[PDB]
Amino acid sequence: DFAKEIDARKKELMELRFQAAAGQLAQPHRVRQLRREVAQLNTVKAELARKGEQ
RNA sequence: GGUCAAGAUAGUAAGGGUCCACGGUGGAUGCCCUGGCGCUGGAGCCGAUGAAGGACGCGAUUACCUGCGAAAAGCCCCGA
Ligand SMILES: [Mg+2]
Ligand SMILES: [Mg+2]
Ligand SMILES: [Mg+2]
Ligand SMILES: [Mg+2]
Ligand SMILES: [Mg+2]
Ligand SMILES: [Mg+2]
Ligand SMILES: [Mg+2]
Ligand SMILES: [Mg+2]
Ligand SMILES: [Mg+2]
Image 1 (cartoon, chains in turn yellow, blue):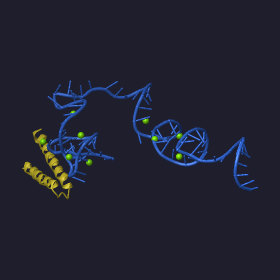
Image 2 (cartoon, protein in one colour):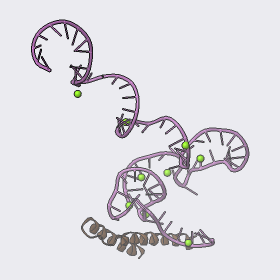
Image 3 (tube, chains in turn cyan, green):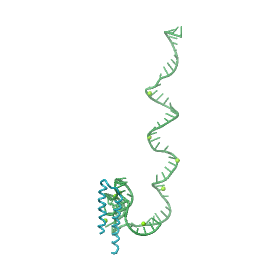
């Protein structure tokens, strides 16, 4: 399911990128926030790798 | 006074020269430190877990440097 959680931020980042290429990018911060949420969402995966499996 | 003769002698500067006054150019000199030099003393290896050094990228807007690496001027934990 974590891939499902990731690609939603991906698609919003894509359509938001399109909007930036056009005439409307009124909240630039929503960009890097979404990128944050991807990094976090992957970093958490790393913590379930070594945990449990040892 | 006036003609006539003889004689002497000034001022004109086209442009120049010396001096002065005033500027332009140009970056010496003084002052300054963001940069260096040396001695002393510490510390002294890095890499197949990918080194040293690079290439390409990551910004709302990014050409250069800096930082980073598709999780890309950052992500998690701890302390101040
Ligand atoms: Mg003249
Ligand atoms: Mg000059
Ligand atoms: Mg001086
Ligand atoms: Mg110095
Ligand atoms: Mg390298
Ligand atoms: Mg970028
Ligand atoms: Mg660069
Ligand atoms: Mg990846
Ligand atoms: Mg903290």
